[PDB]
Amino acid sequence: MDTIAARALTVMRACATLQEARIVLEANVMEILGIAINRYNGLTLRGVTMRPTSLAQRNEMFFMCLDMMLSAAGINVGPISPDYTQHMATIGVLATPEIPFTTEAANEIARVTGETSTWGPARQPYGFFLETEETFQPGRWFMRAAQAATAVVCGPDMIQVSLNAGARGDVQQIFQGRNDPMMIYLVWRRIENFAMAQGNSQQTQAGVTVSVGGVDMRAGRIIAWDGQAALHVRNPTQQNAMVQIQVVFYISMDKTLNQYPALTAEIFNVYSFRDHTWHGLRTAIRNRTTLPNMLPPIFPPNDRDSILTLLLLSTLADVYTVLRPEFAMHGVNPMPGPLTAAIARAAYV
Amino acid sequence: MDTIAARALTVMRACATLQEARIVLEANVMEILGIAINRYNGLTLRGVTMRPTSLAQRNEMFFMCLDMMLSAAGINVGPISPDYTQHMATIGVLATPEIPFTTEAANEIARVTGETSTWGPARQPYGFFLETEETFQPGRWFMRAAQAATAVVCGPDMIQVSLNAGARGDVQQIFQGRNDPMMIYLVWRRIENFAMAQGNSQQTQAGVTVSVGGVDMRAGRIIAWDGQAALHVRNPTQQNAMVQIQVVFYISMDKTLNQYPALTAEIFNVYSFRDHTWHGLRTAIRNRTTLPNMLPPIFPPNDRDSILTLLLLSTLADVYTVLRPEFAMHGVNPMPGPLTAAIARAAYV
Amino acid sequence: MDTIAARALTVMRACATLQEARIVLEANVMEILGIAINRYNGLTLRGVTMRPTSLAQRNEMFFMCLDMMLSAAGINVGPISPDYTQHMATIGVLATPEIPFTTEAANEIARVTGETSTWGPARQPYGFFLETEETFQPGRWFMRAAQAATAVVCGPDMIQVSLNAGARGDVQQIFQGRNDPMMIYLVWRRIENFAMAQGNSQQTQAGVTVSVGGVDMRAGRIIAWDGQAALHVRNPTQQNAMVQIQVVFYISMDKTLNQYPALTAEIFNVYSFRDHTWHGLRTAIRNRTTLPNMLPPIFPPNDRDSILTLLLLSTLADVYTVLRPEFAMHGVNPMPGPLTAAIARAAYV
Amino acid sequence: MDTIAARALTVMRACATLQEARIVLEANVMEILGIAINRYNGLTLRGVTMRPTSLAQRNEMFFMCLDMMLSAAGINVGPISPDYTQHMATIGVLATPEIPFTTEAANEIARVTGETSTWGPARQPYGFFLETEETFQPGRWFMRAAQAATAVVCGPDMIQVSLNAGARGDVQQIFQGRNDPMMIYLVWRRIENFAMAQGNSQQTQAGVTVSVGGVDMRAGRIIAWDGQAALHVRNPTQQNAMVQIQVVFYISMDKTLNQYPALTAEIFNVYSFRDHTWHGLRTAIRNRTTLPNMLPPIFPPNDRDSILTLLLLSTLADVYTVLRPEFAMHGVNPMPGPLTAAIARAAYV
Amino acid sequence: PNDRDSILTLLLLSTLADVYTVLRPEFAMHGVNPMPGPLTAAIARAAYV
Amino acid sequence: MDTIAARALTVMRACATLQEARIVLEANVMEILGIAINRYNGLTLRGVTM
Amino acid sequence: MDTIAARALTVMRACATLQEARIVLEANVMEILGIAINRYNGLTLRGVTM
Amino acid sequence: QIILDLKIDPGERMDPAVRMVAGVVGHLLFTAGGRFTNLTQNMARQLDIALNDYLLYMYNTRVQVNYGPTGEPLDFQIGRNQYDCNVFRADFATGTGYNGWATIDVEYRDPAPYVHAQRYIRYCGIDSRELINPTTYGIGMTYHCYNEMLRMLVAAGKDSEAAYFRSMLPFHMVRFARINQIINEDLHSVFSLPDDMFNALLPDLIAGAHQNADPVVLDVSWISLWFAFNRSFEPTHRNEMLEIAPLIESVYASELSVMKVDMRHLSLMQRRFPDVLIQARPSHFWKAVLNDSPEAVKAVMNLSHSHNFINIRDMMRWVLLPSLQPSLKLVLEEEAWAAANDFEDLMLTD
Amino acid sequence: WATIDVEYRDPAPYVHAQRYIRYCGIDSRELINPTTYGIGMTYHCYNEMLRMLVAAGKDSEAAYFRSMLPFHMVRFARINQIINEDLHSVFSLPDDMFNA
């Protein structure tokens, strides 16, 4: 199954090599396309040439890459063009052991299937306290009735504790319950000049401390916090104190954009316009998937099929560029050949 | 691709034909297996016998069906057993146009792909107002302030309207917003004896009329409501009246357990225990899928892949039964003591 | 006549086998279609190929399936398409003895003609007291003037008897006169806490007994009742009591959805959309029958012609899926797009 | 043993193909019946012809199907007819390995013996609280002495908890002890308007919370509850609150009507009338079994012999339909007048 | 990191990881007790000391 | 030294190409695994197969 | 035009393969460089070794 | 493996006696059996027809001839009891008319030498494991197909002709019992075909689709059919190669693997030393292997290579196939190659 | 019939003709080093020819052509080599006139 995708990928990446037609080829390439196109026309009965020149010859090849790209992603787009017709037989071609697939492609697949099937610690994208409803003003005093120490959020990655002269207390609960972090990197600083409930300026004195699991930590230094340990803040000073603890970043087993090498740019390539014919195509394809047909998912996928598909498409995209195919698509209307940033804007619904 | 799955199915169904050692086979089988087995061992190099008698020969054949089953689905189980290893090449064997499939299996797939690709109207399994947060006592008066007519829920498939003497009004808005019905089947009645705001018994005088889109409707008769027409209730009676409207059943496009013939029976056959070896197998297999590994899906699936997988696994289950395969599996510790309902119960997490 | 219907089904199911162009067919299939198409083209004068490839060859075959599907169900659709014209000679082909039929098809028709020509006991779908006009609040005291015992409906499958201290009496009459049950399964409970005519809570003391045809039955156990025997309720207790008798389910000789194996799915299949060309074709065919042209019959049909039709259409629907025919239909303006859940919804009037 | 059963089944379904006299048979069938009959007439000395025409030839064939049907089910009906003498040696014929069986027949028996020998999770047909002796008024307040929270049943699938202002407590025990559930699917709502101990209307304020095993759950959402976790309800509101919890459906390892594909439809086909000759024959057969002789089992069977029997009869039934047998049966008197829904109604004791 | 050996090690290990995946080896390790049951985000979480 | 690494890398990446029993490995891969394994088993006395 | 860049790229990437002698050139590479270097020397008249 | 293909063409094909006779003979001499085939589809069709004519020949007092819906030869049931001769048609996938039919011939006595899927063909159920007579053994022996042949033979026509068939049973059972011992017992060597292929012959023949496993075309005389039915086979004396055979088998086997091995190493020589073999092409390296290896072995291969054609690709596959029969020669060469990887050890340095 | 036999490719040393003929799409290369096995060499037409010979008349002859096939293609591969390699001179003839 993975092997099929690697093969399909190889073939596309290979056709991608055909900018011109006169050129001499890297023998390695010829061998591929030779076996490929041979078996392809054999079962597909189409007329794809290893050496294209016309246009219909170019389209014909692109259609092949499309056929494969789809069979690999396990997609069936149906009637989306009067010119193109997807041959399910394409799968039978890619299943032929005779067809090779670059070492590169094999490792490419292996990596995807690899991480996709397991988890791993990744630097999360946005601030810790992002999904919060209530937020407070930064540098302002606030003491919840009956308490001596009042920890409270005041940013997407910020909190601030309000201590009374001589007060102490754990704070961990303000973080817990949210996400499922494995480690939270903190860095606390003394709010040297904060506002009091009334509006007056107040100073925090040097001596306030913060200890994790019992051990005393410095101010302004990063701190690996397991999220379970005792996040204790003490105020031995004879005055009101206010400090700020910062979740500079954390790590969880949630898939990020760095799950697979430069996935970002790949996605960009897929979601890029090129032209109406492409746009509509790419869209029409993604409609069979769990992916947003024309706008970068806010949340990076996590299943083999998604990632895999993206890659196939990203490649098929370049293949599109080099071959410069020209064909009709139901519901698509090609506005000539100038193309401006504006027209591209209008294409995105 | 469908052809592929059809073949895989045909083979497993053909393997289940092997019940005894010296029995003669149906002409049909010796034509299928003869080819299949040869082509399989041709790319697999395994020793599959047409008439397995030992155990190692039986395990081998089962591993074959397993390979074809997984392949036909597009599953890469990974390291799940020390005795079994998955050959991705099995896909190539199933793509061989030379291996025939049954008419039965042909139509079987055609149905899945056919329905799973489009939508259709179907009787929903649960009550209309099942997803409601608030419910009122059935047969009790309730008039929202300033209103002459007050419609309210009282159950999963029950609503009751409180009308004042000589009052009238529309009720449709209590039904809308929920789901996306195509046709709701109603049957209204009169609450002859209901409790008042204080607790005293009250009577609903005959004469109250419920009209849909204008035309007047009888009580105790099923009504084809389009969900958009005006559901108007009138109380020309000189007393307080309360009438209940029942959603006997409604139809929508969401797939049900009747999208494919006896889908349920199969699902049961798959989720069934048999023994620890099968249990763990079936589980590990679904771990790669979106389907729950050991407890039936709350909501019936809707994609070809899922439906297919189930049918395949169900068939592979029967194959498991007839072959009596014995082999290791990671995390599976077999208990030989005659297997009982009690032991089976425990295995499900 | 039955022989005719089976042949038509055999042929259709056979045409479904043609998923690809170069695939190897079951010797059985070739033998059949070889005779079928040879004789059809003789009395119809059309050009159907065993191995269609173009589109016109595909339509020609589908048209043949349609001609047979109709001849078998005994329908005359008339002028519904400019491309298609129904040949009445098709019935003569389905009667030609030299055209065999499968064992599966024979056993399929024998089942339809079988249960359709006679009756049988089946669990009815809806509640017993569904076709009632008046309903009372569940758990409320209600004593009809001059009676010591008063049974009254309070649900679609519920009734509640109100007994006075030391009162006894028969109840069987509230059930009688409705439907035509052969056995009504019951389960009675003691309403331990009910509301009085005024609103105060009243307890039902243990001792209240219910006896069927003489013998005393326990509370909370299912009771097979023949609907004729004496359903007697006694109250030797010195207080007001209230018990609820439930009709969990009942059996009658009325045909249900379980008259024919997975008839539900077969129906859903026919009532599904696919595309406009299908939608209209299926509708136009049903306009010749007693079946609703585009919405599931609330009541399961019970005549040979009805069921027979559903199956022929369910199968012809599958034949549609595989052949992917394309043709015009009067009044149908096909939207050549990919098709969405929305577009299908709109197609249903 | 299973082989013996599958062979019998195959033969019956094979005989079911004979709908006419001259019709050509699927070469597959000719092989089957050619062998079967030869070895039957040899070990029984009866004159069964492959191509029956008279009537006695048709009967003879049916008696054969019956003999096999019985031998396969392991039944000895005894002297139930003056024309038919059940020759027990039929088992010897069904054991002849030279006799082939269909792939369908194999997979069929493999399924029956498959699930019959093991357990599995089923949706369960009736309500959770169906077997309860007591029931309370739905929506009515009730507070058992000395408690602050009181759970109480109010329907076949309904319960309601009465909470005092500021009360809290576990509820799970009301579900336990009943049946043997693996997973109970819940959905709680707030009874916004309920009756007090006196009758006056009371309101349930928004703030009540129902938590499963510690985690807080929302109202109007289905919840997977294992039945062992803590079903704790809390009322932080300063008023009396009543909530209804619904068991939409639960799962247990108790066999349901979905153990074998379309088991229901098969059952119906057996319990049908056809004519008196059939009726009595079927009854007399079931008198030997643990299955009800003329009324659908209240509870679905769960043993091999049962299910097996049913199927053999269902098939034997269709065999009956096609062959049109006419014979005498002890204690049965045929009424030749056309047969109506009334005549059949009377035959069922 | 900022030293050759570091970066390098990572790359080689990364690759050796993919090799691990495809070859799916099965062997013992001093101090490691493999829990073969299906594997979830939970069991994974645990393993990180 | 860098070469040693580049070689080691190549070898592993080549071993990663084994997703199937398949045989008839692509020229390039076979050639590599061949040369490699031989020199390895020669100095390791272990028995690795292509 | 892009072809031109692809060539110039391939050439450079190929030259990078030439680490420090102890190398057995990837057959493929040899071929390419040779053709290029050859043509280059034929236009540069400079003495480039492979 | 070897089919009894088409039956030649000459105009002697008319001679109705010869033709009809062969039609009957053939339905008992050969297997259209659903387990494996003996004849061509063509050969059979002509047989069924020759048989069809012999039946509705009727030179004497008529019977009852109930013609069937399909004009197809043998769609007629011959009266009295009406034994429809549709069961004597040619259905390969079934066996239906011709020999075997409702019999088991492909059975498996598990342990047996070779493991070349130890199956056993016992013609018409003749589990011939013992020394035959044939004065005895050809007694109460049914064939079913033969038995039903005799019924149809009388229900239709001639007793005088069907009586000759009853009296023939012994002699016919011995020709077959004899065959079994020869096939099964005698020609059981590493040269007799493997089973997964054995089982694939029949279905691939039906399918029409073609793979390597090719049936041999032996064209036969129409009249020879009769002569064969009146000629049983008693083997006078076995081939002198039998006892020595197994040794010879091993010789060939080992020699082959030695070649494989050599090539495995020679192949990689190019990526190994490019500067030396730039002009090297695959053909080169094995032409050198073939050259330095035993000529007798090549000869054996050439039997099907000068007939079938092998591509360098087919050769590589074969080389890469892991299956080698070890001998002294084998292990030594294998180890020589090992030590010989240094190349400084070969005395040629860069 | 389903093949590309006129393959323009590579700049030609001559220039009248830049084309280079592939009868049955078999580049002489397949001789030097195979492309796809020895079993299947079949080009479309010869393949269809076989299918017809079977369906209609007989296999007996189709077998001859089946086994002959390689010999056939080899002959053609050599022919191609000779044409667009061994003998394209000035007198060769421009693609213009060829296509015309």
Image (spheres, coloured by chain):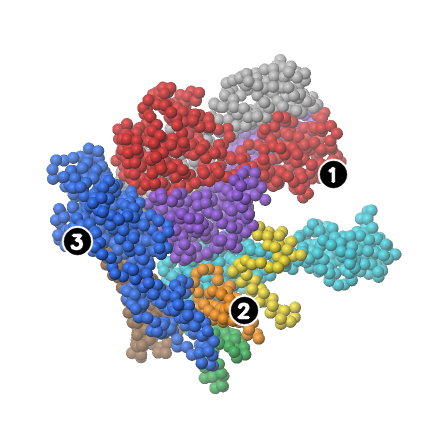
Chain colours: A cyan, B purple, D red, E yellow, F orange, G green, H blue, I brown
- Check disc 1 and give the amino acid type: Pro
In the structure shown, which secondary structural element does the residue marked by tag 2 occupy?
helix
Q: Secondary structure at mark 1?
A: loop
Residue B228 at x, y percent in the picture: 54, 37
Q: Which mark is residue E8?
A: none
Q: Could you confirm whether marks 2 and 3 are on the same chain?
A: no
Residue type (three-letter) at the residue carrying disc 2:
Leu
In this rendering, position of residue D302 left or right of residue D132: left
The Cα–Cα distance between marks 1 and 3, rounded to whole angstroms, is 103 Å
Q: Relative to the observer, which residue lies in front, B50 or H122?
A: H122
> Same chain, marks 2 and 1?
no
| Mark 1 or 3: the one toward you | 3
Asked if residue A275 can be seen in this view, the reply is: no
Q: Residue at x 33, y 26 (%)?
A: D85
What label does residue D236 carry, if any?
1
What residue lies at 55% left-to-right and 73% top-to-bottom? Answer: F4
Residue at mark 1 shares a chain with residue at mark 3: no
Mark 2 surroundings within 10 Å by alpha-carbon count, few (fewer than 14), some (14 through 19), many (20 or more): some
Check disc 3 and give the amino acid type: Ser
Q: Quadrant of the N terminus of chain H?
A: bottom left
Q: For numbered disc 3, what is the local secondary structure? A: loop
Q: How many other residues sit within 10 Å of disc 1, few (<14), some (14-19) or many (≥20)?
A: some
Q: Which mark is residue F9?
A: 2
Residue A46: image x %, image y %? 37, 60
Circle 3 crowding by C-alpha within 10 Å: few under 14, some 14–19, many from 20:
some
Q: Which mark is residue H221?
A: 3
Point out the residue furthest to the right here.
A238
Q: Chain of mark 3?
A: H
Residue plotted at (30% across, 68% down): H296
Give residue D236's position: percent from left, percent from top. Answer: 74, 38
